[PDB]
Structures are given as structure tokens and as C-alpha cells.
Image: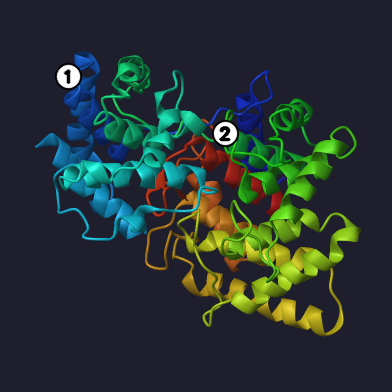
Amino acid sequence: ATAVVRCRTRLARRVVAAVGPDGLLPAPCESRVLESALALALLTEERAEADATARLTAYLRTTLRTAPPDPFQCAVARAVLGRKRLMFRTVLAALGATGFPAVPWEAYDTRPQQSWLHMEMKALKVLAAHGTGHPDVVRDEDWRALLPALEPGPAWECNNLAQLLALLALRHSPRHRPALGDVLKHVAGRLRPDGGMPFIDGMTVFTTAAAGLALSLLPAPPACVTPMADALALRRNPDGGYGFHSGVAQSDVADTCYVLEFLRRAAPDRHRTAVAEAEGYLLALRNPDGGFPTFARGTSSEIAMTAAAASALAHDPDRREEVDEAVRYVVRHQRPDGTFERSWSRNATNAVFRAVLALTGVAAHGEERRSRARAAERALAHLAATQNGDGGWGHAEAEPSDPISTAYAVIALARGPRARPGGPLDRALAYLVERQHPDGGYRSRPDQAGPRPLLIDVPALADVFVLLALAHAT
């Protein structure tokens, strides 16, 4: 058949082969400068784990020299070697790189429902109180929020950044120091082969769900979709949603929508109860304006999450009203140039693809059909207007192409007119065909972020999102 189908086939064989007998597609996260620097600071201050500290030091020097990250992480590494604004500023101040923000202490107090950020901001509050010479300020409720960092094993919620900041704070407390020695051993044991510390253990639930969805959209889905569906469903949280990796108790809308989209196609009867519980999870999060947040009702609706939930819920015709109110929300928030707004993915094409799928997957007629079609047309026009000469898209309009940003654009354009020779979708597919490696895979600059906007590199996601685009486009 076509070069595109042959590319899709080779990629699908590779993705299937990567799924293990437990039904999971492993998705480890690469070492990151920020966490590697914090781990170095912590172990050095505690005069612990000499072998690990030297490996961390070598990792940071190599990475600064060969693949330097964004300027904030660079400044963090240089500090140790020799609200978001408040967080990042206080991190640099704790490492001696700048002054502590002259803010009321309440500036560090956040809603506990945002469990990871809450721990990070409490740890940073303690670091600022001690760093400015006001340790008496710290309240017992501040320390109490940090207690999960003293538990042995992997980090609480698989989050190495939160545990490291918490431990940097806790080492100032005589009452908590008996527990420090054993956790430092666990922290030191996490170093990757390159000597670095990753942000998180991985994103295997997110990645397995997106891969299952891609495989479920092929003409003949492989048999492995069933154990993949099984492996996801048995990991559901009590609220019916899904976190991004095994052992993540905080559910989120992005992960839950990929699981729900996959289960609806590959196991709607076998996992009927998990499907219903995921729909229930989403509906319980829905905001009065018709949008959906990432984690917690009462926080701002987000365009990409609202579009993802619209498409995920659209399968049930009984949810038509909530789905229409979500699509109406997407239309209302489209920007004057046809785009939407970034969040968990750092490229512009991510929210475009989610919006276009919501705008075209829910069947509409009459005035609302025209309104949705016009919005989808402007978004696809934005893609055509910003397409690079090589057929791909980058993270932003002037950036060089990358496969993941291009994959998102392809998913959207597959909802436009039929591909034609030399047209935008045709050229994008040709770009993806050309970027396929001998081993059948893709290598891409990463697009996930956390804490936004700092990039997270989960290399398993490149193959998975390219396969999802090729499954949509063929």
C-alpha cells in the first residue's frame, strides 16, 4: 500500500512489542537538571552518599556543556555547582542564587486540593522562613504537610521534585531529622544510568492509555489491547479517575480522558463499570461555566481539558447536554488568530487538536453546526498558516519541526477536507514518514511540562503520539 500505511505498520509493530506482559507500556522519565541539582544540594548538605553526589555532579556538568536546559534550570545548576514566579524565585533563593521574595508569608499558602503544589509551596515557605532568619514563623501545620517526604520507598505521588524540596526543608527541623537518614538512601538509589534524577518515576498510565487508544483506532487492533485495558482499569483511583503513573492517587482529567477513550473502544463491556466510574469522575469535576479543570472543581476551567472531556463523554448520548456546554465553552475561548492556549503540552498544536476533535466529533446541525465548523476551520487554518517548509510544525510558529508537535497537527487536519497531493495534511504525513528511524521509532523533543512550563522528557510518548496521528489519518 502507501508509504504512510507501511510507516504506520512498522510503528504499530514497535509499539505492540513495547507493551509488556503486565499490559503496560513502560514510560520512564529522563533525568532533569532541576531535580538533579536539588538532589546534589540535599546530599551534599547532609554529607551523605558520596558516590551518588559525584555522579550527580558529573551529570550536571556534562548536561550544561552538551544539552543545556532552559535558563531557570541552568541558573539552578550553576547555583549548586558553585505564584509560579514566587515558587521559582524561592527555589533559586534557597540555593543562594537570589534574594528571598519580600512577600507576606501567606503568599505561600495554596489550596490543599492541589496536592503536589501544596507540598512544594509549604516546603518553599519553610526554606524562606529559615533562609531569611525567621525560623519561628514556621507553624506546626507547615511541617505536617511535609511528612509524606519521610516515608521510605518511591516518592509520594511519584514526584521527586516535591520530595526533594520537602527534605531540604525538613533537614532544618530537629524533630524530623531521625527519619532523614533512611530516606536519603532511597533518594540516592533513584539515580539513572546517566547519573541524574528524573522529575517523576514515569508516565506509564498516560502513555499506556494513549497507546491503547492509538492501537484501538487501527483497522485490526492487536490482541494486546485487552491486557492494556485490564492493566489500566485495575489502577483506577477510588474517585473513578486515573493518575499519570502507577501509585499516583491524584486523578486528573487528561489521564482519565485517554483511559476512557481507550476503554470505550477496546473494552466497553468488559470494563463497563470502570467506564461509568470515569464518566462519573469527569462529571463531578465539571465547572458551572461548562468547562473542566485539570484536577479539582472550583479551579479554573482549561480549554484543552474541556475539549478532551467533551470528546470522552460524547460517546454516551445521555451526556449530550454536558458535552454541548463543553463544546460551546471551547468556541467561546478561541483566540482571534484561531488558536487556543497551552497548558500541559508546550506546543500550540496540542490544544488545537483537542479542540478540533471536540468541534467535529460531537454531531451538530443547524446554527450550532455552522458555529462549530467555522471554529474548526479557523483552527485548521492556523495550522496551515504556520506549517514549516519541511511539512512539520514546532512548539511555536518559528520553531523547527518536531514529530510530536506535527502528530498533534495531523490528528486535527485529519478532521478537515480530504488530503490532496501537496496539501497540508499530505505534506505533514510525508514529514512523519521521513522522520521514522530504522528501528521503526521516533525521537522527538518532548512536549510535556511539569511544573509548567518546565519540560519533562518521556521518550516513549514520541512513538505513541505519532501512531495516534497515523491511525487517525489513515
Task: Residue 79: give x, y in percent of width and height.
Answer: 15, 42
Report the side of 356 relative to 104 (left or right): right
Secondary element under disc 2, as helix, strand or loop, is: loop
Q: Nearer the viewer, residue 447 or 83?
A: 83
For badge 2, the amino acid type reads Val
Task: Residue 253: give x, y in percent of width and height.
Answer: 64, 50
On the question of residue 417 being in view, the answer is no
Residue 47 is marked as: 1
Task: Residue 28: give x, y in percent of width and height.
Answer: 48, 30
N-terminal label among 1 and 2 = 1
Query: Residue at label 2?
Result: 248
Residue 266 is marked as: none
Report the side of 143 relative to 174 (left or right): right
Disc 1 to disc 2, C-alpha distance: 31 Å
Task: Residue 374: give x, y in percent of width and height.
Answer: 69, 81
* Residue at the spot 24% in from the left edge and 42% down from the top edge: 136
Secondary element under disc 1, as helix, strand or loop, is: loop
